[PDB]
Image (spheres, coloured by chain):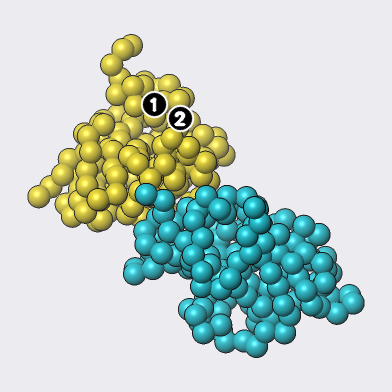
Chain colours: A cyan, B yellow
Amino acid sequence: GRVIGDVVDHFTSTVKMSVIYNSIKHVYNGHELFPSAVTSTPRVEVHGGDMRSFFTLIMTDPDVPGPSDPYLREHLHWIVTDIPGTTDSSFGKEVVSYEMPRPNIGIHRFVFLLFKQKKRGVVCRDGFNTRKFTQENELGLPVAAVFFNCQRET
Amino acid sequence: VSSDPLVIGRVIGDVVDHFTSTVKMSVIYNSSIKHVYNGHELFPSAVTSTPRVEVHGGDMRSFFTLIMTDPDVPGPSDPYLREHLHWIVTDIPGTTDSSFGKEVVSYEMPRPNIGIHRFVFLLFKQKKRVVCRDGFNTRKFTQENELGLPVAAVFFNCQRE
């Protein structure tokens, strides 16, 4: 939360989640991954949540086209809705298809954020705003989040 | 006909169908003044300001729309995000220039990620008087707004410094 206060307001994590890429690789906060390792869609395991609970997952890059002068923030990479508590992203509905990381300038944060929905059951990727999208869809503050660093291949 | 730079550079093919130009236009930057010449390269630092597009034909009672787009994103060898839209100006009167029209999508400066990219400017004649920039498609947008085929076009090449 402390690293991503330009993207979302401070919050207290109430649910645990893991991001697994495919030879399997797990995401650890703040670690760097090469572009070639994240070309496929990952699986996001959602470890908590009550009996009839449902969650939305957003993947965004706030450092565009580079972190020193981010004048196109944010660029949206993925949106999945209606994931049941204690399951994973494959069980939800794909709203915005995954787009593989391909950072232009410098080292970018690729951030995964989870929100609790008010019930079970177009979007431009350029200039996306996480605060405004969650306000408009009544998604509240994050219940979990994790990120990795990534830069271009030489 | 052979040696049309729009055919050789594949603007006709990747972006729009074949067309025969009926109006002349000139794209002028002043970020020294730099005139845009088909297929010539400009550095990113020379194109940070909005340019002036001079519309030389038509008449004052006909209006024209201008679209600026990049079909080589994120790089020309595998352009899986094309096209990226940079600018849209509507209602430009014949014989005047882009400053006299109305801004629909604001100018975004070129900042190409991988390799060398084409930055293309196309002009259409209007019949009659939002838009996500990612995954834009010039054929579809012109069909939906009944803009017909281009009446003129020009492009420059640009890469990261």
Q: Residues within 10 Å of mark 1 (few under 14, many from 20)?
A: few
Q: Residue furthest left?
A: B32
Question: Residue placed at 51% from the left, 84% from the top?
Answer: A2
For residue B137, above or below residue A125: above
Residue B34: in sight, yes or no? yes
| Quadrant housing residue B8 | top left
Residue A135 higher or lower than A60, as above or below: below
User: Residue A5: image x %, image y %?
Assistant: 50, 82
Mark pair 2, 1: CA separation: 6 Å
Which residue corresponds to the image point at 26% horizontal and 31% vertical from the top-left? B39
- Dot 2 falls on a residue whose secondary structure is helix
Residue in the foreground of this view, choosing between A141 and B34? A141
Q: Which residue is mark 1?
A: B10
Residue B13 x %, y %:
45, 25
Image spot of residue A116 (x, y percent):
74, 77
Q: Please state which of residues A111 and A115 is positioned toward the viewer in this rendering.
A: A111
Asked if disc 2 and disc 1 are in contact, CB closer than 8 Å, the reply is yes
Q: Which residue position is annotated with label 2?
A: B14
A123 over B114 or under it: above or below: below
Q: Could you tell me which residue is drawn at 71 percent across and 59 percent down?
A: A43
Q: Report the chain holding disc 1.
A: B
Subunit of mark 2?
Answer: B
